[PDB]
Image: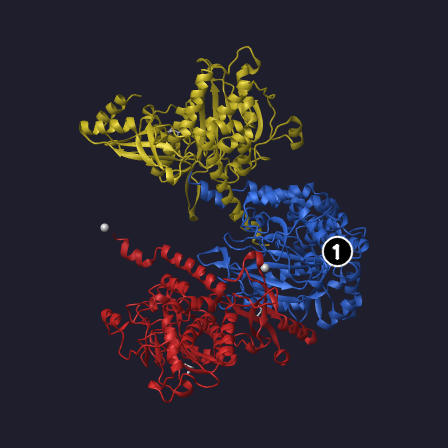
Chain colours: A blue, B yellow, C red
Amino acid sequence: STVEQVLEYVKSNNVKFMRFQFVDILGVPKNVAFPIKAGEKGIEELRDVLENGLYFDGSSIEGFVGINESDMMLKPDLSTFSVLPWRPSEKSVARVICDVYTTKGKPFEGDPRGCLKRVMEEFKKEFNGEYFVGPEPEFFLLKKDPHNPHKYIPADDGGYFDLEPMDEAPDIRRDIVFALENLGFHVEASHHEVAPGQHEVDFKFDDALKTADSVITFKTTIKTIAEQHGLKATFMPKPFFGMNGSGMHCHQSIWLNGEPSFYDENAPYQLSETCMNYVAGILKHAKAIVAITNPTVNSYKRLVPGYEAPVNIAWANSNRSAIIRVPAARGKGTRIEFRAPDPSCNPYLAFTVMLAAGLDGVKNKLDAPEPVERNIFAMSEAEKKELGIESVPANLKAALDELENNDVLKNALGKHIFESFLEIKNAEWDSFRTSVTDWETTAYLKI
Amino acid sequence: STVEQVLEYVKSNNVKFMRFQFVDILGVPKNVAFPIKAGEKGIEELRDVLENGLYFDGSSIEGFVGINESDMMLKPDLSTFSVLPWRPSEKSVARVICDVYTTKGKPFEGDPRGCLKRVMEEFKKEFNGEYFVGPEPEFFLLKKDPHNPHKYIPADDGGYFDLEPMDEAPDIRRDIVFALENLGFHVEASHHEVAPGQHEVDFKFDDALKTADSVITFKTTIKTIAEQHGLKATFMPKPFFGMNGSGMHCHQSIWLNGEPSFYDENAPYQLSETCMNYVAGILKHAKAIVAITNPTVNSYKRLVPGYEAPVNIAWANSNRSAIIRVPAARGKGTRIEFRAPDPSCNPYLAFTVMLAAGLDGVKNKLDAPEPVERNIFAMSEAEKKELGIESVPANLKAALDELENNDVLKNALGKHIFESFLEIKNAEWDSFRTSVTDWETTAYLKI
Amino acid sequence: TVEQVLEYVKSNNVKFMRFQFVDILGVPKNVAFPIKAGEKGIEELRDVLENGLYFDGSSIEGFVGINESDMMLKPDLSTFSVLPWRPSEKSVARVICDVYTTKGKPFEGDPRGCLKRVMEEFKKEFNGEYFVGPEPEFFLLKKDPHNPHKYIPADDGGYFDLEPMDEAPDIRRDIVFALENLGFHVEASHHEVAPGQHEVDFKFDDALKTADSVITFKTTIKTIAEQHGLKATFMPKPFFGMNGSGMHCHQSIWLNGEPSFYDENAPYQLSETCMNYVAGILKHAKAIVAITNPTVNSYKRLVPGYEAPVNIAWANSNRSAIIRVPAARGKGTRIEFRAPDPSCNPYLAFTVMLAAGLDGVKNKLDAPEPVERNIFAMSEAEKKELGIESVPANLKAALDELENNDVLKNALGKHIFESFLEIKNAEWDSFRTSVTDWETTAYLKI
Ligand SMILES: O=C(O)CCC(=O)C(=O)O
Ligand SMILES: O=C(O)CCC(=O)C(=O)O
Ligand SMILES: O=C(O)CCC(=O)C(=O)O
Ligand SMILES: [Mg+2]
Ligand SMILES: [Mg+2]
């Protein structure tokens, strides 16, 4: 946490390189390595770079600054120190996640990490609360297709919770869990998922900032370790048609005055008014939240309306057909599971929009709808229309238009992130709608 | 034209087979061959089948009837008799396009050919008019990719109007023109088009029914002759990205009382009020007409808003940037060119919706907007919004919703064609939005 | 107890705990929990060992719907074991669990709990102990050198053959060590009649301990074979024109801590209880084969009209009948139910066998005379006169018999009985609609 503690770990573990890590607007991690010199002179050089930070070209980073005003800085968060395990042990490489700051030493407006810090500090100042998140980011382990090396296929024909040799990833998951534990993660469980070659490594919930720092490190940990075992890991929301997609279910809850505010022993379903107001806010801005939490064109092939997916804007207890599911655990573990996100989203912006829409419901005391205990997939469109169960947008452009007209998320993300995200994603959407796809060639070349 | 004239040709020219041709809802031609026997017994058998028609399973044809009411008939149109040239000369194979009729001998409601006959007879009864159309259906000649035989590429690296050997299709176009002339076509011109391997074979204008019969025979003629020269012809609206797409510009005009009603010697641009009322009607239902005239998902990659295409809903004189272009020819040849269609559409339904929207403007005497002589592609979106130049839908589903809410085209096509077309195209759209495309795999597998 | 498990984990450096269970088809399913260092890791492991953990039940075959997926696992601490094939440094251990609902009640559709229920009902009513000893045979395969997409047997060997004719003494050496480390009492290991077919026998125990060892055995043979560059299969008939994988079930019931099947002063030294139990198995034989032989391929080994344990009759030391009474007497007196194959769920296989047998013990049903003659040498007209009926010829024929059988419906329960028939009817439909390679060979020429 302090400068002295970080420098003490450098001497103990024999750290030789310090990675000053951060994230671009789309959530892609970016970093620069600093070599630590031997003796006290190297320790005190590292101290200056840890306290004052270092400069970098901001124009090359996505959604940051123009070429005419490119000079920027990185101020390290000393609480996020971690030794990278996949790197060598002798002359080890450690990391330090930083906050992007302007030349004048002021936090950068277009920084996703600073955006999440801002809304969390505002929440702690106004309500004395702590926003806790616990995601379930799923991924696919791939191998080259033997019939064609240019294409990739799943690593095994395994199912949900399957055992070896049907599940060919116990060794890959073993090293992933060991690597995460060394990085400071509290791993809860690991297993094979529904689709072939799909896996899920869960970890303990924590405050939104520590959880978002963990999601970035988790994605790198999964990809780097897969390359060591001759495989390629992908967090694509739907790499293959006809099989389950990678989903990042976000279990979340707010604790006002160090108490579980979502729990109420004397209430319906043992859920407090604060919980219902929060759920109402998420459901209100659901069509706009999916623009940030599902930012790829491929995300709307997993999260596809009219088909089995968490597309139905409604909440329910122990039901995976609705967008929100309230797990049966009560007391401290009382929470809500927002099932719409996929691991393709920027965690810093995903937790910001979820907390902003949720707090909009708490501030205004919005009324939540009744829980749809029935299976929503079995219902007909005329029946769902009578109940008022609306669906999330069918494509990326449909979600961007909803985000653009939403003022709650515009204020939470800020003018810089809101406008740059829409501009980057509209160019991405335009590239998709103009390209001639393989489906079109298969269906229309014969005509 | 009469039964005796057809049988007299069959007797002398040694015709052995008679193809009873027709089209499904999507415009795909369908036929059954009838062998003609020698002597008077064979001619009297053919006479009965020509006058009374023959039965067929309607459930197997797309957008026709259910399995529980499948029995249907084909009543030949003796005016469309033609000798297929690509077939042998000795013991030749002749064709006769037919009207689909129900078991009770009544014209089938879901027949595209009967749909066009109905609206033309209604126009001739109400106004004493004749609807003339002259299309320019472009196509691509393809060859297998040498680096991969599973994919196809253009036959040559030729440009617009290029000469041999740069243009490698003079021999292919030569045989196409000879085949069309034998089928009764009045070929006007033939040449290489802008994109590599793209070509265009133009033919004289005629009444909508004779023109739609010619478009079906043209598509078959271009594909069969290409297979003879070891190539594969495709009428796909956009087979390759980054190069021009196949467009079917429809030059059209209406003649009330055997006179060119679109021409007016003493008027602005030498164009009559009837012409302006017709143009106003096309521009009014432009967003709904493109559902029929551009029925494929790929059509919206050629006809793509925001990019160089005939997407801007406006008319202009000798300007190819607008949806309508008024060619400089005057007098009898005074006409309007609807540039939005591509050869993937059903010609019988395309001419029906164009005549219905155009006549809606003539009946109500709608006011047309001013001609946009300026290049519309060079204009900015804010400038086009001030002028009021709206754009055609960006995708197939966006056009189907416009067609569904349009009552003018619903009545012209009829309940059977209107509902079956929307149902077939919505299932086609759902297949596209759920499939994982090659673009998505290229862009998101790395994440 | 909880402390016994925690003390082994503390000293031996165990790092992963597999919470294992089975779906309706007997396919094993599990999730790994990482054990942290120090007292904090041991206290975290204590919580998850006593209270259990949650899992998506809808994704498991034959469990619950999507709108009611919250389910838990309650570890049976007596089933603790170290997985030998996994690494020794930072070792991996397992714990077989019982599926429980959100309300903390045993799940009705759980196969393991289904066997516990009938065993506890038996010990409460008759004070008995149901002992079973299976012989789950398997096939070690290798890719066909003429085509890598197909698999063939590993060696051109025979029954009990010696190396180099038998090329699996190295593979069976490691299978026996792996099972010994898991806590198995291995009795014999050898090659079987067909090429590449092998057998590893283990000592009998109570039906639950045996069913846990059947799941652990199936995984052990497959993981050890994949280490030696081969692929093991417990398919009931992978190749035509040779023996199939059979899982003979040597079973017996001990009322009041004594061998009730033995009677020193009786015919064949077999008690009245044994003859009543055999009469019950033969009565429900047409229905038991639906559970003990649930695959379509099972009826290609267990094929009527051809040499197999298809004939519904009993005999001493005769392998032609469905039941064979081994010549061992005293404590080792038992009956061998020969129809089963290693493709079945053991928990459901022992449940239907005990329930059908106890139906004969409760009603005191009379068994027929033993058919000491070779049944394969008999004609169909002779077998009809004696009353020797045969087991169903296909999967769908067995599912109809199981559906009408009320004795096995109540033993499996409304949840397991209905989901099994639904899963197997959909499986049968997939087979009868598909155009098989036999049809292409016989009818493409016409
Ligand atoms: O496979 C896992 O999920 C974690 C690692 C493990 O259990 C193992 O090494 O066997
Ligand atoms: O090439 C054409 O467009 C028509 C055929 C022709 O002119 C030729 O045979 O050279
Ligand atoms: O082959 C067997 O059955 C057990 C192992 C053995 O005997 C050997 O290692 O030679
Ligand atoms: Mg999951
Ligand atoms: Mg024949």
Within-10-Å neighbours for mark 1: few <14, some 14–19, many 20+: many
Q: Residue at x 54, y 58 (%)?
A: C65
Front-most of residues A379 and C176 = A379
The residue shown at (54%, 55%) is A244
Report the front residue among A244 and A97.
Answer: A244
Image quadrant containing the N terminus of chain B: top left
In the image, residue B162 sits, relative to residue A270, either above or below, namely above
Is residue C104 shown to the viewer in this render?
yes
Q: Residue furthest top?
A: B266
Identity, as a three-letter code, of the amino acid under mark 1: Asp
The picture places residue B250, in percent across and down from the top left corner, at 48, 26
Residue A376: x percent and y percent? 57, 50
User: Is residue A110 among the parts visible in the rendering?
Assistant: no
Residue holding disc 1:
A99
Q: Which residue extends farthest bottom?
A: C265
The percent coordinates of residue B310 (x first, y second) are: 55, 30
Camera-side residue of C239 and C417: C417
Q: Nearer the viewer, residue C34 or A100?
A: C34
Residue furthest to the front in view is: C363
Relative side of C435 to C373, left or right: right
Helix, strand or loop status at disc 1: strand
